[PDB]
Image (spheres, coloured by chain):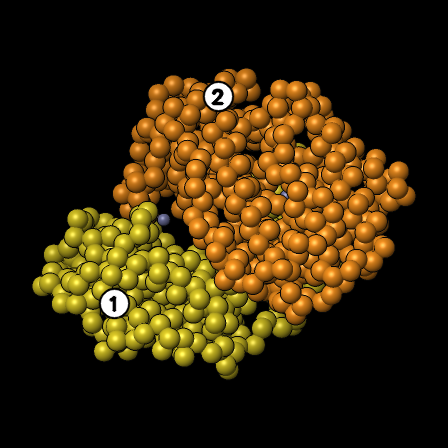
Chain colours: A orange, B yellow
Amino acid sequence: STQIGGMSLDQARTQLAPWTQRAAPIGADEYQQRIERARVLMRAQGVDALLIGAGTSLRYFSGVPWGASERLVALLLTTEGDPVLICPAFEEGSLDAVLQLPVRKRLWEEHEDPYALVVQAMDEQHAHALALDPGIAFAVHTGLRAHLGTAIRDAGAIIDGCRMCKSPAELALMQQACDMTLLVQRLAAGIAHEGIGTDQLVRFIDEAHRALGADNGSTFCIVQFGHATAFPHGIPGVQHLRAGELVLIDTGCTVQGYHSDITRTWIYGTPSDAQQRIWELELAAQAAAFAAVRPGVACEAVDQAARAVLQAAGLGPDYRLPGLPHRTGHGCGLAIHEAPYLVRGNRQPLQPGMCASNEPMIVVPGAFGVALEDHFYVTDTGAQWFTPPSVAIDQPFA
Amino acid sequence: TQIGGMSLDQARTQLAPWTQRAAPIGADEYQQRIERARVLMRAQGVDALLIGAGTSLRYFSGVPWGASERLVALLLTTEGDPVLICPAFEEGSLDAVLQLPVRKRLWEEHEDPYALVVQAMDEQHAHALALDPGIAFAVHTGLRAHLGTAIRDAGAIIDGCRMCKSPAELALMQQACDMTLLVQRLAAGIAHEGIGTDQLVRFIDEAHRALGADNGSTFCIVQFGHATAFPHGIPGVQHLRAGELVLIDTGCTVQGYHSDITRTWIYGTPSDAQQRIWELELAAQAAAFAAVRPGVACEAVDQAARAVLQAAGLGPDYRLPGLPHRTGHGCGLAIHEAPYLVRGNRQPLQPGMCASNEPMIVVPGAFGVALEDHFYVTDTGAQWFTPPSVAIDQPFA
Ligand SMILES: [Zn+2]
Ligand SMILES: [Zn+2]
Ligand SMILES: [Zn+2]
Ligand SMILES: [Zn+2]
Ligand SMILES: [Zn+2]
Ligand SMILES: [Zn+2]
Ligand SMILES: [Zn+2]
């Protein structure tokens, strides 16, 4: 019982120095490797032009970390030559400061049509088969259609085909984000006390993430007590902690854009027999999902392995409650959620380097939920946890 | 006096939660918004409207969630309660935030939610879908998978609703702006030699929270000295020096409605160039405002700011020193929305429309001066949400 409650705030703060032995940032050669990979997958799908919008995919291919806006900022990759970077002219200086890939800047002034620029660049290289970023706003399709009459493919297969398998450098940045958030999770359980507010934990978790050297504090944070733990993504309203209540904390940060995403569920005080049984079951379901992971295995097979555990114990089947109402997991990288998804119907075979979450949450309607979440990556022979799973309902940390 | 002189503790004495808070949007108003979209659909020959999670779903239904890879959407047709497409597992969380009566169509994880959209269309003999232009392109792919018919862009329908704000919408934006204006005042107040950009950003977030914003600072740009020449700034912490301009662009939300205010002021003594360019910026912003009245095109407001700059020998067009980007953007449940105060936009301003007025001057290699205050259009002219600055060393009226 040494992990829950024993700690005061500035006592926690003494363990919040900036992270050391930081992982190296992605280098210029790796960006080029990603471009070349995209080109292979473009050729495979019969595509000769690829438009990537501002967001995690632009960051992946070029280093530009900006969120998307109403203004088109995009990378147009074609079969050869430096890719074109379409960008508002007033942003050129900011752009140069973040670009990690050599490009050919095509700048547009505010009243000019940036979609016209994209097609002009396509015509220059005689590209006539575009694949468009599935994350880009629909407005961009509308813009391109005024100028482009040929088929516009969904670039999802190409983008996933690149991003799903992580390089050692990517794994190391993810590892760093995970090690940090694990510590934040540990300290959050430490300072928990009777009456503490959910808002207080959220705020501490953000503070901790910042102190440890995350990109931007907490990426997200879900904290729920007692019966509120039955809602997987939570509900509005501040709670205050009472003995006997489960505490669910799902949170993460980013390091150079790469996400951690960890959930811990633990008891504050004495657990009921119901809470203990469901907690142990959650641990076993997560364990089973992990044990099913090796190269070649269909993603849905991992989801099924977790459900098989629940069913054997009289929960489920399928998504029936009490049981697991959502997928077992999601891929994770530069985005909090990305391919491959650990979900029924997904026949995608797992390959070394693939990163996904393992979080087969059990919901007991009207009562509580137990969610344990740690991420893994696929190895040559099996899997490797980014963070080791919890041990007991009152021992969230291995 | 407005710049410096205030300690952090004295600043915090002014940070009680906001009082005289504006009312949240009522059930009746969400229904009015739906009815407006319906006539806009009819005006356009559209009989189905799909709205994705985001500021537009919040606008029509009250649901505030960010978009995800899982479709969460509102399908509006010509009659009946609109359909809400949503993951089955989210139904509980959904019920806690929905402000509109809907017909739920829930999908399990392995099921095709786009199939549910098209089934709902088929049941109502709808064949003319307009799609939310803010939605992920993956949704277009998913719907096209099931539709051989045209999929139109829903921009005109959505803007046709959102551009003109109701009195309740104005009051929520007004509160957010009043809050952020005070945060701007306190930020200028605690300024001192050596203070970091990172420290100002943290205080401004802390302040927005204490005041009762939705989620601290929505965003925050703080630049010093030469760094003020970059409209959206650049990486790196700075520490304040005498003789440097400070630019602060920040905002919060209240019930989702945005503030968005920029102040640029001198710490210490300004140079002649800084003073002249500061004055010119106030004048450009003033002229843009004076141009606003019903019927005036958005581009004419942008042109009024540019004409001031060109008269003074800056520009023309976007040439620097001058104004490298548009004069402003609409603002509401989104930080950026229609109508845009930009060349080429012939959209006439009408009463209720809300927009920023921020004709920033950039002086390459030297500095930039940005003043930003938002306004709404009235029957005869315009009304500031916040009053413009007075001088380079008096950021607040
Ligand atoms: Zn959710
Ligand atoms: Zn999570
Ligand atoms: Zn997760
Ligand atoms: Zn997601
Ligand atoms: Zn920017
Ligand atoms: Zn602004
Ligand atoms: Zn603005």
Residue drawn where x is 64% and y is 38% of the image: A388
Up-down: is A254 above or below A48? below
Q: Nearer the viewer, residue B91 or B127?
A: B91
Mark 1 belongs to which amino acid? His
Q: Name the subunit of mark 1.
A: B
Helix, strand or loop status at disc 1: loop
Q: In the image shown, does B21 or B117 lie closer to the viewer?
A: B21
Residue B313: image x %, image y %? 12, 56
- Which residue is pictured at 47% across the width and 42% down the height? A255
Q: Is residue B249 left or right of residue A184?
A: left
Amino acid type at circle 2 is Arg
Q: Is residue A305 visible?
A: yes
Report whether B349 appears left or right of B241. right
Residues tagged by mark 1 and mark 2 found on one chain of the structure: no
Q: Secondary structure at mark 2?
A: helix
Q: Please, which residue is most extreme toward the bottom here?
A: B20
Please report the residue visible at 52 percent of the width from the left and 60 percent of the height from the top: A11
Question: In the rendered picture of this protein, how many numbered marks are placed on residues?
Answer: 2
Mark 1–mark 2 distance (CA, rounded to whole Å): 51 Å
Q: Which residue is mark 1?
A: B192
Residue A274 occupies quadrant: bottom right
Chain letter for the residue marked with disc 2 in the picture: A
Q: In x, y percent, where is residue A183?
A: 55, 48
Instruction: Determine crowd level at label 2: few under 14, some 14-19, many 20+ residues with C-alpha closer than 10 A.
Output: some
Residue at numbered disc 2: A37
Q: Quadrant of residue A62?
A: top left
